Image (tube, rainbow over all chains, first blue to last red; front, side):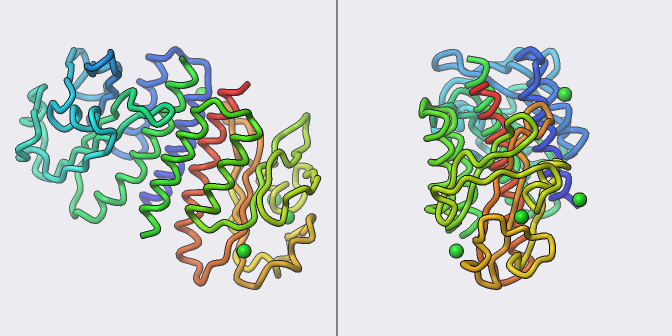
Length: 162
Length: 162
Ligand SMILES: [Cl-]
Ligand SMILES: [Cl-]
Ligand SMILES: [Cl-]
Ligand SMILES: [Cl-]
């Protein structure tokens, strides 16, 4: 049951983020458990450097990639600017998908992209972006609720670590 | 749509808890938004002092009531002990309901009790307990996930405020 895995992964992420790991190690471990609990094969967390977004931690294909997004740039960039999420089914062939890392070639037709804002005091400080396969648009919409929760936990972690 | 209100209340709670309100005002405001967004008319957040839980904040019937729970004592005490949630339909008539606060006589048969742990580093530091009417076991299960999420946000907050 997916909901059961979602409950458990949220609990586990809270345990990690209330621990004493470094900022970078904490983010990395969150993405690792998204893989091991929820099957998220590729993901990253990008952090604001003023008006630009830079990948701070990654899992899967984004390892050893140094990428940046400007406000309005692609899916992640729009989420950064507006502080509202984007849920994009079959992203491989979506027009707004900027595929800034050539990851598209590595996706299938079922992969969706969900990008959610990370907010502190209601202001966007980062974005979490994940790729995961879905068979129908309804299951995708449900899954977004969980990724939104994780974005919020990350917002509290950003506050915690100043 | 309920899912939409749940998403919005989680965002709002994160905004409150990453702000600068006092510890007690923050907890109270969380319970206030549970009422305003999700219709939760009676609730409390209890915090661990030594090895006992004490009510730190309350809303509705629990206002101005001093109540302590020991590990294993009643429904809230069991969540405290095991660090796993309880979802009790028709709590008014449940054998494990200690009805410490005598709220029982004010509840209808439709009221459920949902109690979720508040964990820091995986250790139980408190419990959030809510009472709310439901018309079927199914919608109760969905609602439980959201209360669990709020317990996790509160865990982050407890870490934030030392
Ligand atoms: Cl840990
Ligand atoms: Cl009520
Ligand atoms: Cl009880
Ligand atoms: Cl027990």
